[PDB]
Image (cartoon, rainbow, N blue to C red; front, side, top):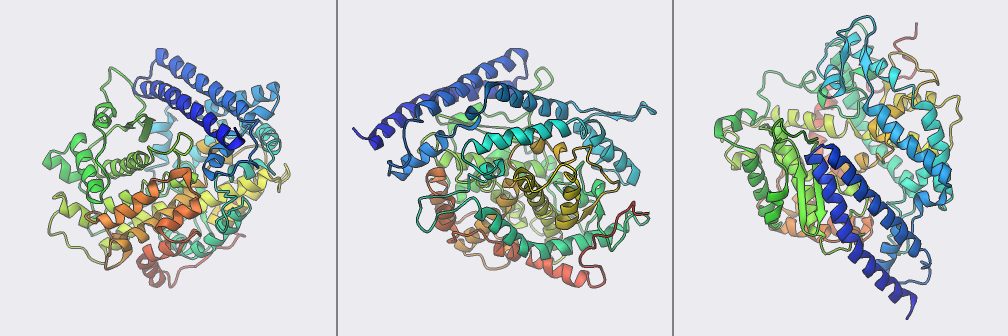
Length: 597
């Protein structure tokens, strides 16, 4: 007859009512992704608005239950994420303005078209269009045109809408008892009420800017090497003392740096690793790729997947008769139903993608017993962190040799491991400072460290301060360059893509030491060792029921988040760079600019 028992029965009624409508709402979404149809575009809308109304009404009926007089930390964990008013605190007109701004941001970015009024042939789409010329072009102006002009038609029309977004989200957060919306976004990592494990939202910056203080060395040699060797590509434009132009970072912006490898190979005469020539000869299909990826998880002790998983997942493009957006996504429909979406093809990268998205499915399989609010990762960067460590063990030549794909007598030397390390670090570390600078800018603008008149000046300063990237052409206040990214335009959280990597190496190191590997960490494998899989499962089975510090402790043993596994993983590459960069300019100087004439 007290608050703690009334909260439990209310949560029982909520979870026994949230689960079944969540299934109904996600089924329509999956049916729309499989079948892009007008009849389906409204079905998921009806279903999603029903569940949106459900969560709002349950949030309202949960708001008479104080958090101070409930002691059970489980019930408190359920209540703290359900009590969140979010958009409920603002007026109807402000809610209308925010949602029109929301569906305008996505619309303008998605339907942004580039064209040349002087040359009709210079008109192309984004995928597989505009990114392609930013993908495989070796000319400077070729990338320059669709770099500056990309933000000419979309990088101007979101500046005032985002200016209004900043101010309305400030009240979005302040009315909910936060300092800023930057303080609302850093709220997932907040842990309170756990003695010794209590984590505050203000400590996130204190830890992130400290962890970057040990990542800066490796990155400055990466930048020094890349700038030293791109003068073989662009000798007449780029200084080997200054920094790099933004249009040569691999994509329209430069988040991922996979695209530089084909031009920045360490050794060219060696034969790079690939089975793409191996499944064509040996008759592997999407079924068999998944079946062999399953054995990876079976070896470490993880249970076999559901019978319905195979009969409900989508594996191969259903021809031209039906058009399905098949971005690689893992789907947890609940009620024991889980599916995966990807247009599978016969290539090694699709094998790594299959493993990466298969880890997500297995991880979500682990916490089925958790309630419908605890059926999520402890932190946001934790869900994509459990899914890539399989991929790091899926690219090891030892792994490919035991399955009969890779040649049994491939010689592995100091030139093969090192090129593998360049391929991975240029991809997994080339993204960390860019994620950090982006979220740091979001935090100083959302706390209001900047006025209007230097909104983007102090943006290119931190690109030229953190990642060391100069602009080919100066930008005045009129545009909006940060908004060009999809995650900024639709306003997601991004530091999940800096913190996921740093969980990745901690987990990999702890796991393959628990597997008793003798040798450098960059090749250690997790298969055929149940003692590490059982340790990992005892972590995956908690999910959100425990604080992320304790979740890190039960595996790695540290409540802190560390870079030491990162430096162990890239120590051999670090060593190559030291004696490779004896004559290059370690570091950068801010005075340099390509247009400083």
